[PDB]
Length: 102
Length: 97
Length: 105
Length: 102
Image (tube, rainbow over all chains, first blue to last red):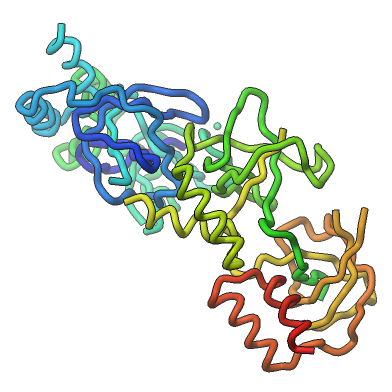
């Protein structure tokens, strides 16, 4: 039985960063998704903790951006809007990317 | 730092829990275990990503707390306006009642 | 009083062998999810891969998934850790998993 | 093509053997058990009533070489402590300890 739960604002996925790999908010990263696939996502933030223990977080595979694909302003607005209007931050981020750059 | 909090291209991403002799249907609130930490949730659907072996509590409603109409509507709006089903459902309940 | 839990004098790194699925790849230093005992799984770190299992190549189950594309540890740190485990007589698994949290920032 | 995986296994990594009907041993006693073909001498750390593998799926003991515990009641408590406290493989501590103790 699939159940819905009162989750925290941006429902994000936590990935472990192998030793010696570094990323900053606003950067795209290639990460695993479901048993064996890969997918592109954007780092919303990086902290020192996750609901699950570090040894359980799959590691990021590659960082696609050296610097933020989004502007410091645009980024702040994007995250704002996603939160204010109750929109999935991933949703907002990837949808806005094509608009902003194209 | 260690953990990277990542945004992903929008998946209704729900949590699956095990139900012998306990029955529930869509639109019903249920108490279920949450992390290495009980909590209320709403049954979105009822044969799993991970092993039916490795979190399972009870059904708080015999009948759906939402109308067939209401539910259809709420699920639509969640989808149409890009809002997490959970958010819509839990926030709608109070106004509803 | 049926089961007897016996300690044996085993070699340097007492490690557990698993079979690699068809089309799955992992190298040393990588964490993998594997079956343990009857009910469920657990996370472990690949210490090495080779064509040398001291058991029937069918009596051993297979990896479930690899959580790391690349080594979660550095080439040196890794050299260091395995040494430490051996030199100071500490369980390799103990060293690796305790070291991970401290190591990862 | 096999991976040699290291797992964070609980405190005393021990090996479980079935005690043939009518065979009896006490902690601190050596026993001959099957291993891999060959046999080997091990020291009984304890006797429970269940293991992490199906109750009858595990090889039986072959012979008990000590009817009396080869270690003192105290030395025993000490070594088991030391193994745990200093994170040393119990079988390592016991077998290395034996030659010096004797």
